[PDB]
Length: 69
Length: 196
Image 1 (tube, rainbow over the protein chains, first blue to last red):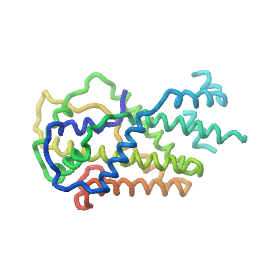
Image 2: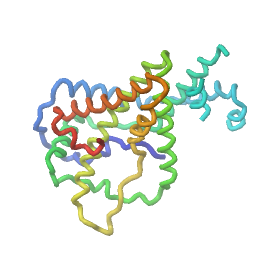
Image 3: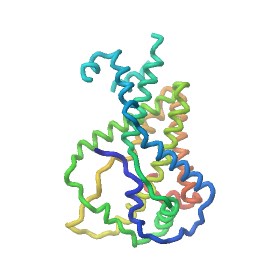
Image 4: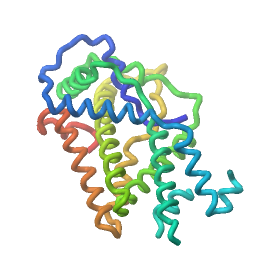
């Protein structure tokens, strides 16, 4: 299937790159990256019920979707 | 379809079904974005990308994005992109309900920061591509959903009948610019990204 571009694909070219950035990392950038890591972890936590329960609640107000289901 | 119709159009049980629809829409958006495992020292690689972009380094190995993808269907990808855009538009509209505002706002801000991170690397790749000469063996890169459907959703939300939707639409642009400034370090070289 099709998804948005993953970051690992974009940082793959720097796999063997052993370099130090010119600009020293500051506190705000570190907090930004920590928040991003938290969001990325939260992204991959979708269970089956998250999709299935709303469908079996919403089928009770529309008959065409119940037919489809 | 039914979830969007139920959410974005207005008994005593309506809030229950609206909550169910919102949950479904959020789950579908998360599934469409996808899950990724990034390296441990990602900040260093991001700053290396920024350094390469600010200069014009020609030693970037982008052979991974020169491989043709000649097995999938382009039309299917277009349809998926349109579906994701519809989902984002519904999420933006959801800001007009006081009980849903905080959740959708947090989710949208997180998505905007994620897409800024994507755009920086896309800029590096595009800068490197402009110098490569012609070659018959080479092809285009992989197929993916364009993360610039957010721009179209924001465009379609800027003239909404509700003030909250317009304010959120403006706040998203502000947030993306602020994230770009934070990642770069200073606002000097931010206008060099191809997103603007």
